[PDB]
Amino acid sequence: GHMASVTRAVFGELPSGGGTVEKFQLQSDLLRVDIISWGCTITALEVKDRQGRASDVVLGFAELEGYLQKQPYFGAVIGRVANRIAKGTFKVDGKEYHLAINKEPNSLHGGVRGFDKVLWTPRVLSNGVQFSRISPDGEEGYPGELKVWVTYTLDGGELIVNYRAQASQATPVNLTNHSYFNLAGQASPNINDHEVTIEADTYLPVDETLIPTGEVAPVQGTAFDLRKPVELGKHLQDFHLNGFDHNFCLKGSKEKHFCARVHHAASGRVLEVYTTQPGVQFYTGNFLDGTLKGKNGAVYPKHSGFCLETQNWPDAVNQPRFPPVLLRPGEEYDHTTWFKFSVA
Image (cartoon, rainbow, N blue to C red; front, side, top):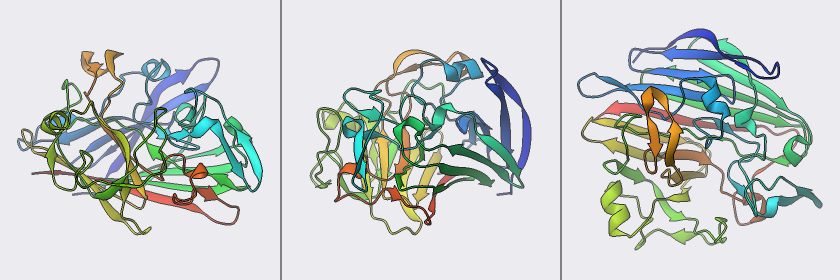
C-alpha cells in the first residue's frame, strides 16, 4: 500500500463559458481514482480482484456531457444538505426558511443547483486533491455563506474523503458522496450477489414521501437487520423487498467508526467503510431504469449499483430527536469517511 501520485488534465468545458473542468487522477499501487472539479465527482474507481485484475467499480460517464444530462447524482458531492427536507422548509433561530421543491412535496439534495452541480476550485496535494468553494448566503434558500473544502486522499487501497466547512451564519450542513458501486464491476447488471453488512441497531422508517416518520426503529426482527452479512438478493426476496433507501443509525461518537462492509466473493473484492458520521444512507439504485448511456457502453438498469452516503440523518433540521445538523459561526464542520478496498 503506497501513497498515491497525482496527475491532472483537462476533462471538459462547461457551456455558456461555464469554465474549464479538470480531471485529477490519484493512483497508488492498489487503486486508481478519477475525480473531476465539477461537483467533486468521482468518475472512475479501479479496484483489483484476486487475479489482480482491475475493474472500474463505479457507475459514471465517459465525458462531461454525460454528467450534465439528467442523471441521478452519480458519484458527486452532495450539499448544502443531503437527502430530504420536509416541505422544503425549516426554521433556524426562530426564522423560517424555504427551499426549492425539486421533489414534490419536498426538497432534495441541496435544491435545484446543489453542490454536485457547481464547479469547485482544485488544489493539488501530495497524495491527493482538495476542492474548495464558497456557497454564498442564500444559495438555494440557505442562510449564510458557507465555505467548504472537500479533500480526497489516497493511501494504498484506502481512499479518504474529508469534509470541512465554515458558516457565516447558523445553517444546516450535511455533506456526503453519492457514488454508485458495483464490486463486480461497473458493467455488471446487478448487485444481487453482493454480500452486505451494516453495523447499525436502528434505522429510520419513512413515510409516503420518504421522510423519516421520526421513529428510531430497531432493526431486530426486521428486513433492516444487516448486522450479520447477508446476500443482497436472497435478502430482498426473503423479505419481499424492492431494495433499500433508508438511513441506518450508526453507533457513533465523532470518533472514526465502522460503517459497513460489502463483499463480492466471485471477484473477492471487499469494500469497508468507516466514518465519523451518525448515519449512512444505504440505497440500492432502485430508481435506475436502464436508460442511461454509461461508460463502456454500459446502460444502467435498476439495481445495478448501490450507494453508501455517510451523513447526518435525513430531515434532522426538523426532527429534534435527531443529531444536530446546524453549523454556527465560530464552530467548524468536519467529517471524514474512509473507503477501504481489499481482497477476501
